[PDB]
Image (cartoon, rainbow, N blue to C red):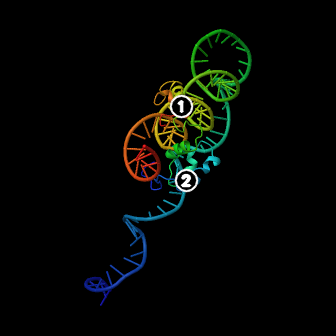
Amino acid sequence: KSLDPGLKKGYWAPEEDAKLLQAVAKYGEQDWFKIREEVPGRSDAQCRDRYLRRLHFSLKKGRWNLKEEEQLIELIEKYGVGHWAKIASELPHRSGSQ
DNA sequence: GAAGCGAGCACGGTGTTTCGTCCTTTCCACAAGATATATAAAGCCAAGAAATCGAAATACTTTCAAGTTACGGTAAGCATAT
């Protein structure tokens, strides 16, 4: 993921919306090593988290309404603090990064 | 005619070869060696087949090199809010 002349450190999505989203239907959620051979400028390490955080569906998003605080409470009430504790390993997709 | 000058032939030598034993064999022969055979107990020598153990080959364990999935935490420049 570094010192590579073929990688691109860009920020926007030039051609990515196709080059990376084709893997959605082309290949499953495993063996990312196969896709990196066709998409230039993109590495597997960043590709995994990009694919994950861009196409996910079930996430607590929207405006902070009068009913979201109970959601947060029952979230931190599942197993513990969650954000960094080891319980983060079983919280489904609620990693500390977010 | 017999005394002074040139005269055969028996004889006496080595050296070389021949002849004829004595040599040790090859070969042969009369008398007597195991040579067959009967034990039989003993322990050891010694040339064949069957069971056993050492070496190791190909095989599978196991352990040690590579490495890429999956995973958890911080930092910058564009967008957007009062």
Three-letter code for the amino acid on which mark 2 is drawn = Glu
Query: In the shown orientation, is residue A70 left or right of residue A9?
Result: right
* Element class at badge 1: helix
Q: Residue at x 57, y 52 (%)?
A: A17
Q: Residue at x 61, y 51 (%)?
A: A22
Estimate how packed mark 2 is, as few (under 14), some (14 to 19) or many (20 or more) residues with alpha carbons within 10 Å: some
> Which residue was labeled with disc 1?
A68
Estimate how packed mark 1 is, as few (under 14), some (14 to 19) or many (20 or more) residues with alpha carbons within 10 Å: some
Q: Residue at x 48, y 34 (%)?
A: A96
Q: Residue at x 49, y 53 (%)?
A: A12
Q: Position of residue A25 (x, y in %)?
A: 65, 47
* Pick the front one: B12 or A67: A67
Nearer the N terminus, badge 2 or badge 1? Answer: 2
Quarter residue B82 falls in: top left
| Subunit that carries the residue with mark 2 | A
Query: In the shown orientation, is residue A27 left or right of residue A10?
Result: right
Q: Position of residue B23 (x, y in %)?
A: 50, 44
Q: Position of residue A59 (x, y in %)?
A: 56, 37
> Which residue was labeled with disc 2?
A16
* Pick the front one: B46 or A16: A16
Q: Is residue A3 above or below residue A76?
A: below
| Subunit that carries the residue with mark 1 | A
Q: Is residue A74 above or below residue A59?
A: above
* Element class at badge 2: helix
